[PDB]
Image: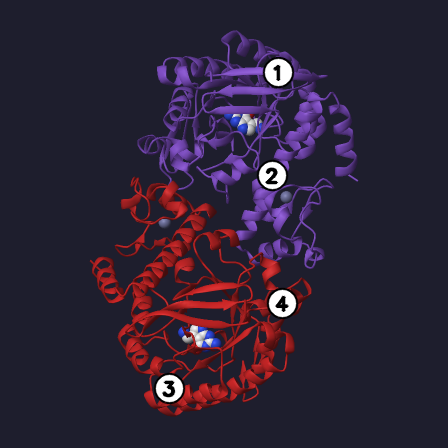
Chain colours: A red, B purple
Amino acid sequence: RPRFSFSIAAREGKARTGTIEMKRGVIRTPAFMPVGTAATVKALKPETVRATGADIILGNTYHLMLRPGAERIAKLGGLHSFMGWDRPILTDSGGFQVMSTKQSEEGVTFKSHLDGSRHMLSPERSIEIQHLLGSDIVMAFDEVTPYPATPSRAASSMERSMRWAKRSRDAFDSRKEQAENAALFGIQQGSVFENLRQQSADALAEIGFDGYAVGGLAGGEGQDEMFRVLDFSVPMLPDDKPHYLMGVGKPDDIVGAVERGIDMFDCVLPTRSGRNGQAFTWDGPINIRNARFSEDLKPLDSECHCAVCQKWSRAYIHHLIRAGEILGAMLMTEHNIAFYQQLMQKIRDSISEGRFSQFAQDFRARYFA
Amino acid sequence: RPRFSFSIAAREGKARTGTIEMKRGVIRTPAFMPVGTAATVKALKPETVRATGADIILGNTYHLMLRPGAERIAKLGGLHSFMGWDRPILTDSGGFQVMSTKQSEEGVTFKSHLDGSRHMLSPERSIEIQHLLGSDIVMAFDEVTPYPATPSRAASSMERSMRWAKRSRDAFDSRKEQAENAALFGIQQGSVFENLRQQSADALAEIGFDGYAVGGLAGGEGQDEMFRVLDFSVPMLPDDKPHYLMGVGKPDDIVGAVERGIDMFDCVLPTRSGRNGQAFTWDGPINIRNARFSEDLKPLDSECHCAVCQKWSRAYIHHLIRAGEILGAMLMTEHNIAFYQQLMQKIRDSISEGRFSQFAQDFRARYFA
Ligand SMILES: NCc1c[nH]c2nc(N)[nH]c(=O)c12
Ligand SMILES: NCc1c[nH]c2nc(N)[nH]c(=O)c12
Ligand SMILES: [Zn+2]
Ligand SMILES: [Zn+2]
């Protein structure tokens, strides 16, 4: 396999389906990436993550640098070896967690929430950490402006992000092993403003990246506004490269974003809300803690092919979650990630067959019935 | 398979190895039974429990009656179906948790620690709950005297326990489906007193049970005293039936107890201490939280055949446990239960080959080096 190759096999309107080939494996798109916060997809062995259908997982640079440490992971053989996942890993840059402390044009300094120790992030240090981890898809370090943002502040943050995108590009390229084996994605900023999104897209395309993320969304704006911004923002990006919507999201957000040209997604929703008792179903989410499930012998979802729905009832999972049992988190998480992967597979198949618009309509009618 | 058949294949001194055949499966002895508190062996799917080598698991009557409820489990198809374990299950009677609230010759009434609701246990109700759960090995309901106990109080509790053993026998026998498909074990009491242990053994043998537990030990007395009581107590029990030491224990306790004629064990140690960071190894226990393991690439144990030791390092598990990650509990628990099963297999093989005394000596020399 090549370092990086994105091929589009089929299209329907703005939606695309295809593959990204990388040294560690093939990624089917549109793709959902389970989030591995601190070198684990919470409550799942990597083999279980793979069995759900995941082709790639996300690791968080900010968290890994705090614990167990980037240099430590490198000494131990890199993130893949450390956690036992041998397929591609995308790492975020830290820009989001920095927003979520001294800031300057050079970068940011901040105190660890775990120990109070002082840490620094910059385009150069973020790229270095992602190298030490050994990630396959490296994200440029950006400045993420909060929502809502004034036009002036959105412009200033976008302009800084573009300067930092060039610094990220140069840092990545200067490291031979990284440049030859990994890929680098740029991140579009500009808040909700069309002119700023255009300037950002133009700057990123001039620099040149392997993929382009739409940054700064899902920050409080709501679905209608997010979709409106995607309507104009995604077509600004190079058509022949993957389009990644960071930190999205709910199943309906994913379907609508694919309709608008997005190829890649990550979010903590299926894992985090799984541990809290929320299970995704084709008829919409349910909260398994609800007393109505205490004697319900049906599986979490009636059609789901996952191992949890093959083997255990709602009633059992209800009991586990109510009791605070670890197995409850395990089963809920496996089902939710499997559900997300089945959603992505239905999306890919429907685009390939030219019936994605119908799928989206049918999905929504049932999910929100 | 028959309802119950215990066969002894080989002996060495007081130690025995063999099999218990039951309708749901064969149990190799000496056996270790992982503890499923509230219908789950904590942090493990039943298939993982089985893969470690477990032939039977324990369920706690006291906890299950409080949550999710015995009648509820029965309505849902019984404990095996509910939790997805199709092999034998032994249920304890509740006598221990009652000690751990109004007491009388009829039984005990108590308040739920979860809800404050009032509950009752008696020989008849305990046997009924174990029936509703559908367990394969049912334990008689006893009164467990605290350690230390005066001779008078030990005698009174033992005598009550024997009256309750007869009531348990009669309750079990009066329920056709239970009598025909499950087995019933009696529990010897008498604290540390030889004459009381003899009276108890004689009473239980007169009533007649499928198996005999040594109750009331591991209550604070320490290993030397426990071994001393086992020295005289186990030979009092019928030789041709299984001997079960309840709530034991550490690997060295197990080896010494097998040397004294015990066939079955259960304890929360490998699961509970696994979640806390303690990992069992042939060179003794380690606490994986210790900073010395932060960059240790070796598996938890150098010889262990378990999947955790095949795939992940001490350094990784150290990180997971320090971070409070669920996967840490999962991996520690799987390894510890697998370690216990490998210990039982080495015990069985060494007895079968007439080299158990040597095995015990070699095990101790290395474990305590
Ligand atoms: N939802 C926006 C988002 C999530 N994660 C991110 N990481 C980075 N570096 N930038 C971003 O804009 C975002
Ligand atoms: N270690 C003693 C023990 C553990 N569990 C028990 N359960 C019962 N019914 N009786 C007992 O004596 C014990
Ligand atoms: Zn499912
Ligand atoms: Zn192991």
* Residue A49 percent across, percent down from the top left: 47, 55
Left or right? Give the position of B62 relative to B355.
left
Q: Chain of mark 3?
A: A
Q: Which quadrant of the frame does ligand 2 lie within?
A: top right
Q: Which residue is mark 3?
A: A197
Q: Which residue is mark 1?
A: B8
Query: Real-space Cα distance between discs 2 and 3?
Result: 56 Å
User: Which quarter of the picture shows residue A220?
Assistant: bottom left
Q: Residue at x 61, y 28 (%)?
A: B147
**Element at badge 4?**
loop
Q: Nearer the viewer, residue B363 or B212?
A: B363
Q: Which residue is mark 2?
A: B338
| Res. B12 visible in picture | yes
Q: Which residue is mark 4?
A: A69
Query: Real-space Cα distance between discs 2 and 1?
Result: 24 Å
Q: Residue at x 43, y 40 (%)?
A: B113
